[PDB]
Length: 70
Length: 69
Image (cartoon, rainbow over all chains, first blue to last red; front, side, top):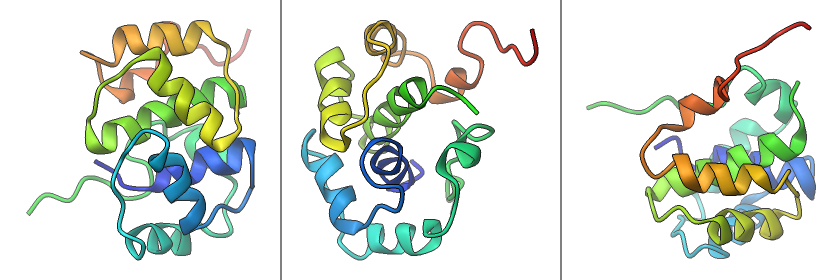
């Protein structure tokens, strides 16, 4: 409900501290979660240049994009 | 900050919540291995326990919500 932010965080947490769309596809592909190759490249595009832990260390929820209503 | 393990389990659950798909220890483990970021295994267990009913926002509390010591 917050999009590929979390996948980005995962990749950056234990593989690559600057994840990309392909890394997202990777992470979600492993559990069979579908992803649009622009949507994640976009989330990453936003995410790129942030300190993952510190981001989520006060943001286990509403990761980057807060649920879009309407 | 947290422990990247705990936080990793967090995120595995996060991706799981993006499709809101089934939550199993092996599911979270699959995320863990996919990214390459490992967790304190009791977390994947307890996560799979709770996240089938609770919300990821509960992880921010992690039945403690402590700051200093």
